[PDB]
Amino acid sequence: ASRGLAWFQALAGSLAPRPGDPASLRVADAELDGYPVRFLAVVPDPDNPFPRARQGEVGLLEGWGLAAAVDEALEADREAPRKRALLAIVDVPSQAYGRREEALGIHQALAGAVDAYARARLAGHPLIGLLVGKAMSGAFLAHGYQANRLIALHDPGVMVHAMGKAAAARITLRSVEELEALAAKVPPMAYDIDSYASLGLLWRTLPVETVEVPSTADLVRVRTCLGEALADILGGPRDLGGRLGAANREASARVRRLLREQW
Amino acid sequence: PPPQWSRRRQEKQRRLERVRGLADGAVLPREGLVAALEALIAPGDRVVLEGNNQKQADFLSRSLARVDPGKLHDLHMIMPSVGRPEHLDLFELGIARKLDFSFSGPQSLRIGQLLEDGLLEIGAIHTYIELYARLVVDLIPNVALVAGFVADREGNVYTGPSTEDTPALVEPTAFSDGIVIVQVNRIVDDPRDLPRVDIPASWVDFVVEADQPFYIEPLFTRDPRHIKPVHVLMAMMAIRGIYQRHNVQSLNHGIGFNTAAIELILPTYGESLGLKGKICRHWTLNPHPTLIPAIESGWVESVHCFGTELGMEGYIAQRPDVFFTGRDGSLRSNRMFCQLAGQYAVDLFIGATLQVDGDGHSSTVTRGRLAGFGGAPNMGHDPRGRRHSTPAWLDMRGEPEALLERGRKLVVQMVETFQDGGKPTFVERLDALEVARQTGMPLAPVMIYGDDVTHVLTEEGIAYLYKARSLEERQAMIAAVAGISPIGLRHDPRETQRMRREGLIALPEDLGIRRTDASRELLAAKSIAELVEWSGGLYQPPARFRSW
Amino acid sequence: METLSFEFPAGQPGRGRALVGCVGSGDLEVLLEPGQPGKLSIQVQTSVNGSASRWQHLFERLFDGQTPPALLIDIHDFGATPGVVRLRLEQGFEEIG
Amino acid sequence: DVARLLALRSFTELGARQRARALLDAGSFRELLDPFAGVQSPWLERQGIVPQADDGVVVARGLLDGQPAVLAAIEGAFQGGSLGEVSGAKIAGALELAAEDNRNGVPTRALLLLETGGVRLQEANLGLAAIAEIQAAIVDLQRYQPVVAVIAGPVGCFGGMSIAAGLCSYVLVTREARLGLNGPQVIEQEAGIAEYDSRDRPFIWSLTGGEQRFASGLADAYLADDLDEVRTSVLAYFAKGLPARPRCRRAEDYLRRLGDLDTAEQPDAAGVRRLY
Ligand SMILES: CC(C)(COP(=O)(O)OP(=O)(O)OC[C@H]1O[C@@H](n2cnc3c(N)ncnc32)[C@H](O)[C@@H]1OP(=O)(O)O)[C@@H](O)C(=O)NCCC(=O)NCCS
Ligand SMILES: [Cl-]
């Protein structure tokens, strides 16, 4: 039904949704080289109470639902010897776009998600974001961008951005033609994963044999990668400082530096 | 002037009559020299022998080796530099037994060996100005064996561009009833043919027309051909990460290709930052040929010199506004006076080195090789006696309106993570420690102490140690720029961003320096020949560096 | 002299070729060609013996948190310092883009 | 009366730098990375867009009742208050440094004046990365001090920063301010003119207005647009400290209430106040 769903069942075994989670969520605990791992993924739910959230969007339920599952695991390992890692399989086309959604405070729903993941990361839980499909705007802020490390599959279906070129062109006052034009000259404007990589926001990109449904070869390279990523995280700084190494984020780093000088 | 209170005067007097026949006046016969040396020197005398960084009293130095080891034994050699072979020959022949030196040239594997055989005994490794200072306290000298260019029959010596350590080696000897012998290239019968008097005749006891001009070493001259792009990468970080970030107005450059790199990319990389005249206006430096384009580009206002680099004399006479020249037109170097300035009057020192441990301790002393310290310890330390404020000096203060917190001299240690021979520079223990145990050295021979270093500069980046709150934090900073050396392998990379942001370290990226931008194309002069034509034919490189 | 072989997880094959440096004492030569996707295969011939562990660290650091293009890198080293080496690898990698 | 009308002292009538100086204690204002630093957007000139010297954000130190504080005000006039690479890093990096002040004994407060259109689509991925770091630093900081978000309008607060608004301990709003995830046009665009009307201004405020958001608990204070009254409420909320249990950790209550609602039909302004 979506690359997220395909990749969740392939990495977690459990493909049916837990009871208690919205049908749009997919949670499942498991192990990854003897390390406790909870897999989270947002997938489509063509029978979602909200119509504007039936193609995998991260809407009201998906938002709070994520805040639920993470806070669940947060208090479990409140005591545990080893805080369990959270692996976010990211593949969400967008935020839910709709009246129902805005009226009920969808911005607040996704804030519950961000708060959860963030508090988890801060506590010692290792987050890892696996970009297997689309990762857009608010949806990705909620489900993914609190990660200690980001991993994307190298593939044309994997895209990162904040708005569809239709809407972006409108707000901005440009044609879809000049965006795609500009998107080659301005890496932060581009949708492809190569341009994202140049922002040095990815800890690793890894190409695959069959992105739609991982092959036993793929799933082992991906599983190995997560293992390596998880070890890099453990025992180290928990902040997002690792996302400042790239030359295209030169300025982000310079601002933080100047800030401290004048602080 | 009573007997019991003038015993070293009557001893000098006894010595001058055992050559009264052999010498007429102050002039000594070139082919009866070794005879005189056996008469003027006594066994056990403290002898100062000119082995300067450049000027060598090679004739005296050789004649003293062909002395009879039965008439002269247990001599105490005091030499600022031990470069020449005749020098360490004095010890194997049994003429000399103790040595007090500062700079050990190539002779480093030898001195170590001769010491281990019980033929040579070392007092300590000094730093020039320290060793001079001793000559009027601990080590008052008996004989001085120095060198100049011209001398009249009266005793006046013209040391010229090569004055160097002479005025400091001679004075404590002449005025303590000791004996001063100066070899010259030429005696003039008419004294008005002496372009200048550098040493008055009343300090000199005898002059000798040498068998050939005194040997001059181009100790500091560096062939810009050998400057690799890694050197040019550190040179850029020095100029933007240090000279510019602290507004260094005056400085000294330690010997080495590393600082030659800096000198040569000032009129290009320095220019591209519009820094001409904004930094490095005043120098306490040898007249480095690699500095020539920086002079011509109009960066350098003043230069006071320790000595002279062979071949630079003519260039310098043509630049009286920059260098310190006599009324005769030629340079007047003064290693004592320059060294003093390099400590008290200059904003920064920057130099290379052979080893550093995790604490920042630096040294040139390595397994069985007793290298010297040269001028590094004098300029590689925060001069605690200084009070005069200067822009850069003050920038080092943590809390700038604490009136009791004093400033610090910028002390930069500029080195690649690896010595070329696949040895790492930053090691767990200094070799110097083990060399100390096996020499009865009371404390390990460290050239520059870790607590004295303010900047550690590497092809990896800059560590601003002057900001270290604790020793543990200092060690953290060193390892961050230490590469894949055993010290640098202590560093955990996830910690780098923190250290960068906090401004503890600076990567070349942090300075606006793309690493791959480092090429020889930044070198103002690409060869010795190109150095000659910035100088417009005036620089006459010594045969060693000529390709024509 | 000894011959060392390495391998690293990488991305899509790089776009062109590149040559940097020369096998003179103290310098090294680096050949960069596009390679098999997912793999970066390095081959090192060095004049320095038992440096293998040293080359390992150099490379791990170079590729830490930055996935390289899938290339075949042939290095010929005549005793260049890890500093010089690192520099030429970056020259080489810059030219490949 | 008329003297009162002639003496109004509107808050929204001030620009970012004016608001900042106006709230921070008299005389403590000290701007960091000011327009003379010339730390501007590296991505705009190449696209033929004129850049602003401070990239549309005013970040300044100072006091809030003699308590050390940092303030980030977004300027709505510039690119609608859109955050870009430099814009974002001014805010995130400031919250990050406030947090490190709490860990070193200094009880620094973070006051955010949000007048933003979310990610600057002309810097899309670099501004969105920034907001994630803004969010992360907001959470990290609210383990020590509350973050007060002030949304006064005119632009309001949309996109990624509406999610950052959510994360905040207290959210003070005026009547003119809106707080939504997606801007009215964007929804109309993606979902159809029937699902949401970008031209229907009274409708847009009826669901996402400052009044509506306060009457439904998605906001903590419903301020009038007066300079003094806003400062007063700001100072007051910082003084209450961290909230017992903030909207973010109420994940199951809302999930419960949403479960109750009959989603089969379009909720209205009032329908939403009832469901909470
Ligand atoms: C913010 C918003 C609701 C305000 O609209 P409004 O009150 O009618 O005011 P306007 O539409 O006149 O906006 C004025 C300016 O803001 C700019 N702007 C708003 N959001 C922007 C964005 N995300 N990126 C770039 N520019 C933006 C507009 O381009 C416009 O440009 P102009 O000053 O040159 O005329 C509206 O601009 C909007 O819908 N923004 C989209 C926010 C969003 O959904 N974010 C997605 C990214 S995470
Ligand atoms: Cl010197």
Image (cartoon, coloured by chain):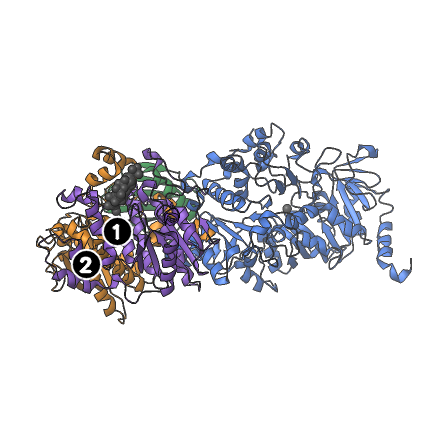
Chain colours: A orange, B blue, C green, D purple
Mark 2, chain letter? D
User: Label 1: how many residues lie within 10 Å, few (<14), some (14-19) or many (20+)?
Assistant: many
> Share a chain, discs 2 and 1?
yes
Depicted A182 relative to depicted D230: above or below: above
From the viewer's perspective, tell me whether residue D7 is left or right of residue A213. Answer: right
Mark 2 lies on a secondary structure that is helix
**A251 or B234: which is nearer to us?**
A251
Q: Residue at x 61, y 27 (%)?
A: B537
Residue B540 sits in quarter: top right
Q: Nearer the viewer, mark 2 or mark 1?
A: 2
Mark 1, chain letter? D
Q: Residue at x 59, y 39 (%)?
A: B221
Total label count? 2
Depicted B447 relative to depicted B221: above or below: below
| Relative image position of residue D45 (x, y in whole percent) | 35, 35
Cβ at disc 2 under 8 Å from ligand 1:
no
Visible in this render: residue B179?
yes
